[PDB]
Image (cartoon, rainbow, N blue to C red; front, side, top):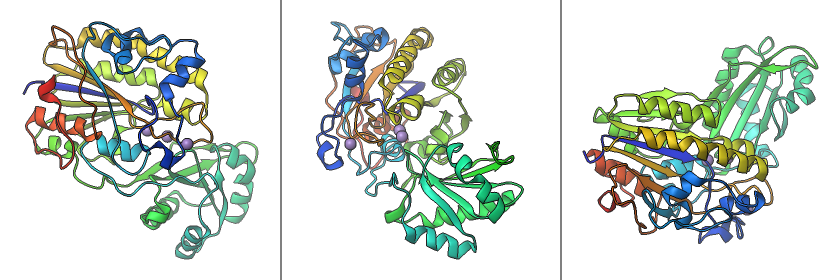
Length: 391
Ligand SMILES: [Mn+2]
Ligand SMILES: [Mn+2]
Ligand SMILES: [Mn+2]
């Protein structure tokens, strides 16, 4: 192998400006990093700048450098959707024609009617909410009736809440598996069905760690599957395992924050493995993008950037670091959905003695998967063009 280890970091939702097809999605004008940089009066990301972030595009506080540490470009999404699953599945070598749906006004009556009819249970609520706002509103009615609280969120999710002493935990799981089957339907296709058991009494409800997420498997065998099948390590960090429903994963390390994610990345740098370490930094998306909070988003990007020098210090000559994103989520954009944007790509190894250069723009996120596959000599994905030889 050219590289013994590849460290792939997805800065979830960290877009670098509207894609050519942005108008289809109502995303004209979107620019995640650029709008954050303006809000911050100049982003302080000296380490990403050293890698070549500003060579991809100049933004407030983010300038080009004469000699970027590694190679740089941006990537265009080919798949139909702009959701997390679509982006990640594309990154690992697929093409996804059918988009996952988000439901800001709640779910169609048709879906919920079928769920009632298959379960013999009433459904109440139907609408976006936090799992503490909706329990305050409807938790008592749930206890007294045995009905199911259905709700959504800013992401492609269907969430089902029931009190554990009224609807047995095992029943709630069965109901969620039924819903997972009903939602394999392009009209209603949610990324995740989520069991949200709760306990307590009116005015004091709390969700339990008995939460269960029901994900769809990727629509194809990914580069991860191929690495696992050839006895390589595939270490998933953060939401990565859930995003791929475990497919091709050999070890999974849960994280609770972006900083915890960077700690786990450092943990893998200390591991003797051969294969792929794959991190998702989700806070950008979950805490800041969807909540339209550019200040919090800017601060998180600066916290992330400050962690990078330790990573640079630990990378070996036969290590490759890849930094990218899975879509945009512009915190100054209307509504609460993702934004259809290019994503940055930075590729760095300490073995790059003369530093990096610009890569041709990547026409699909699958160029990452193709590059990983070629590095490790496993079956090449159906989609994507490797840039391994360019590095
Ligand atoms: Mn939009
Ligand atoms: Mn995402
Ligand atoms: Mn999201």
